[PDB]
Image: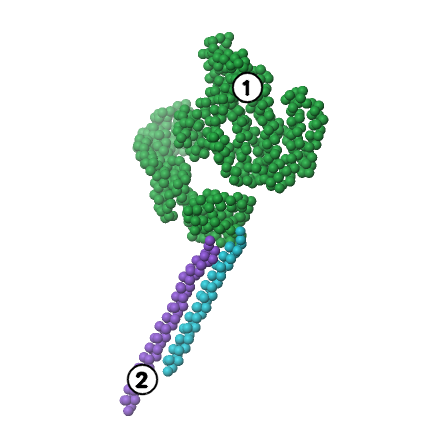
Amino acid sequence: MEKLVLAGPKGRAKELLQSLQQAGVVHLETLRPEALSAYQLSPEERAELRRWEAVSAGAEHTLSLLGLEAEPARPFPEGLEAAEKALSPIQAHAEGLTRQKQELEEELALAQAYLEPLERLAALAHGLDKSPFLRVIPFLLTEKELPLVEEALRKALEDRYLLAHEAYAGGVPALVVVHRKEVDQAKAALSRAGVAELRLPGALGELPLSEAARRLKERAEAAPRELSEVRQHLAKLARESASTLQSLWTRAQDEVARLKALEELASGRFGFALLGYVPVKAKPKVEEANPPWVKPFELLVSFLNTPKYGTFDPTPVVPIFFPFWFGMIVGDIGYALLFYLVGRWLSGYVKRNEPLVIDLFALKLKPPVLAKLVYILNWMVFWTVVWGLIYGEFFGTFLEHLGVFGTPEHPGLIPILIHRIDTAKTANLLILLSVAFGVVMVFAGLILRAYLGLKHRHMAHFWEGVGYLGGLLGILALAASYLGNLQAGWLSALMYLGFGVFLLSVVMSSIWLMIPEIFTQAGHILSHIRIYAVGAAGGILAGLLTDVGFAMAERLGLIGVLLGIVVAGVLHLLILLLTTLGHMLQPIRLIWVEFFTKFGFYEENGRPYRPFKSVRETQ
Amino acid sequence: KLEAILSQEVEAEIQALLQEAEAKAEAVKREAEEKAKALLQARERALEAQYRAALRRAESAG
Amino acid sequence: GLIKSLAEKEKQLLERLEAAKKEAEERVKRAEAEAKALLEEAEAKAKA
């Protein structure tokens, strides 16, 4: 029976216990810090740990050069000595080749720039680079520059000089021949003009010109063939040993985590620490612990198991998200009913988009693993696109059929030839439908706000959640009078007054020295309304722009527009596509009002648990 | 579990250690008898020369 | 969880060490005493 010591926080002592019991563990006992301070690494342990990181480093280093870094779940179990022996030739070979290839490219670059200048300059000073008699100065001239230079030399150096030049492929590299001790006269003339000397880097420059010129030529010629050799070798190493580097990194990495864990236990700073024994079979288990709703619901199960407050776990969040999210596509012939294509790319596999090839092998813009993690989301994106197609047929209930409006059941050009959602009232009712869902979400949050202090036993939050619902009576009163118009207005001026007292009554037990901030709490209500409203109005608006896009915008609206309208269609389409991507951000902006500004949820100025954005990202 | 079991794993290494330190406690008595022995082999032998000499002297005189 | 596991485990490992020391010391002593007691007899024999 293998012994384990496990540690974690005090808050989740119970939750840890419970995960463990289900997993299979027996003999659980709590430990005090004296018992934890006994497991301090030793010089032999620490020496292996520095070394294990050294393997980890060497692996990243070499693998990055051969291709791309990634780490597979599998390890390859070996001793240290074995690890050190496998990496050392593989690293040596990669290290040599990447320097050799870089050296060749730099080398080739110099040879390419300067073969013709040095060749021209060498010929010019043939035998003149080692005769004591004469001194030569090489320098670069451009065509425009040459007359000035020539005059300038001639005043400096009289008529006891030879200036000859040959043309490389621009201007000329020019060479002046002067007597030794009239060297200074010639250099002064160039310096004064602003003409710099021509030479090569390092040793090659120092060597006579001819030697340099012949070599340079030969290196321009030779380098691509040497570069081809080194590249082949580098590829053959990459095909065979990319996989091995990845597996050595994985074994070392686990081992690093293991040893670091132990040193971290040793200081005994952990709150809750447990002792237990597991059987051999048990030892693997102990350490571990309809498609539209159930599939994302399955991932919410890991967060069901973990509560950190007296508020109920963030499981309801996903069905609250769904109506508004689905309801973001409600366009016509030109948007919603064509959206089908867009869904099929992500949940299926096409070649149409470049980084998407076989989605079945998880190939995306995103990393291959990451794409596998958001398969669940891809399915929900598909359901989103499909629910968007249906709300296209919803849309054509009020924009087509002769049973609902006078608009043709089949137009003579293309479906959705007329728009009847251009009448203010028809459009308004769908807006007012969304607004209602926002009132509900305000209620959902405010029950959740209050619940936190109920099961966490914190009075301040409790008082805030109950008192705020007083405000809700007053929101619903005022609303009835605006939604039905002549419904209240005298039955919510009198009643409003007893509704306002409920608003603050227990808020004053809580104290609250942000009395003005209640304008912003009403504002938060107004933000859920204004976001559902935009999702409705902006939804219909996208479609009404298709009125002069896919129907009719040319001639008299005769039959020929069918094959003329596409002129406009191609332009609008993409513009529309771009702006409706902005409309799908309205959901997560909706969650952030409530989630991130405290109404029963963790978030508000940091705090434990992770943002709902990172949670829904996979779901 | 292990508890007193783990302390009987110590009580085993420190009997390993105790056999080594009973292997000094054997070596001391061994080097002490192997020593003593040569000192009475020496005492016997010295007296013998000095007793062979005592009789030869008393012979030559007699 | 009971504190008796971790506590009484320290004090049974600690107790083990104590008995290792005790019989290391009272044994080293003994060995010297034997050597001595022999070497007194090695004089008592020699004189005879």
Which chain did the image draw in purple? B
Q: Nearer the viewer, mark 1 or mark 2?
A: 1
Amino acid at the residue labelled 1: Leu
- Tell me the subunit letter for badge 1: A
What residue appears at the point 41 percent right and 37 percent down from the top-left corner? A70
Residue farthest along the left direction in this orientation: B60
Q: Is residue A15 visible?
A: yes
The numbered disc on residue A2 is none
* Residue indicated by mark 2: B51
In the rendered image, residue A252, in percent from the top left (x then y), is placed at: 41, 44
Q: Residue at x 48, y 59 (%)?
A: C13
Q: Where, by quadrant of the figure, is residue A150 drawn?
A: top left
Please tell me the numbered disc located at residue A541: 1
Residue nearest the viewer, comparing A134 with A247: A247
The answer to whether A169 appears left or right of A323 in the picture is left
- Give the residue displayed 66% in from the left and 29% down from the top: A473
Q: Chain C is shown in which shade?
A: cyan
Shown colour of chain A: green
Which percent across, then down, holds residue A51? 41, 47
Q: Secondary structure at mark 1?
A: helix
* Residue at screen point 47% across, 24% down: A386
Q: Amino acid at mark 2?
A: Tyr
